[PDB]
Image (tube, rainbow over all chains, first blue to last red):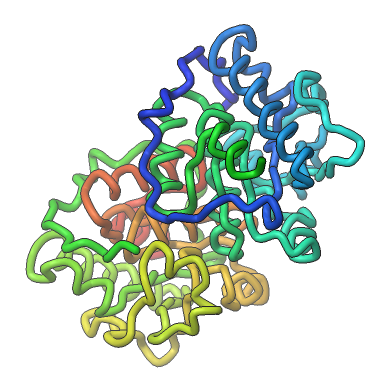
Length: 209
Length: 209
């Protein structure tokens, strides 16, 4: 089993470097949901939080959720629970060990508001073992705007599952972070060419206001 | 909408260049299933079939299936159906168009045997809208040995779903092909470090005989 590495700091990808979208979907405030993916103390503490990309990530997540709430867009947070039953954790243990035992709280900078939804996360994808798919169908919302960590792992897997489940995923390039700038960029490149749309925080704000 | 490109010829990755496995799972003939992923004339026609990696891919898929059948390992083929209903095809149309309208047959070199299972494929992952998961649970088999095309798309998505569904995916590095040698290698690198195991045809034969 690997440990999540001590993540070396890196610069947030310039907006000019975002990969070009193959699809021309537009974020619709009537049909979208914002997903704040696993922004727990445990996952973010693997970085030096005073250094890029973490301060930009947290301020940009706040920019996304504030404009989402003002446009009546539901905000959903995912969080892994502490001391996962080995039978429930299953194959994750083989790669990553027993998982978090503490620091499960969402970081205070992006703390959920009373009206926000909070789901217990069990796999890379936010759709596995959660009510996300059925709840989005109930809400008649078919667009998922994704922010959080880590790009090539949970963000990628959630975007792939959304796309295959007929939900349009929009990954916010300047509102995610990863193990490195290369992993972060490669996540955006894969999504834009094979599984969804890559947008900036300003493009999200512009589309929903 | 993109067309599957005219795939240029490339050399099958040397065995010495395969990424190192992070997990130490071993293919068990009592617990495994071989998946021949979308090896249809339609998908294979995008390469010049007389040039590398196609002759070696077909020969290698055959080495895998013959060894599997001799060890009593079920062999499952996935195939996309022609003229998919736009409502069923959904978001795939935005990236790839209406999909295949003919050439749905499995390439004759690796044509299914009477005892083999054949499922109708609808998404990148062989688990979506198929009986694969429930049938593997019925068979009490929790290992999926993956061969076929294309590495970074269907093979990758099937491996991620299997892993999240508690099924151990083993991608056969010299029994897959992709859009390029880089995509092929990057698929193996991602699987080995985040979602499964990467093995050679000889390692599969050795494990099941």
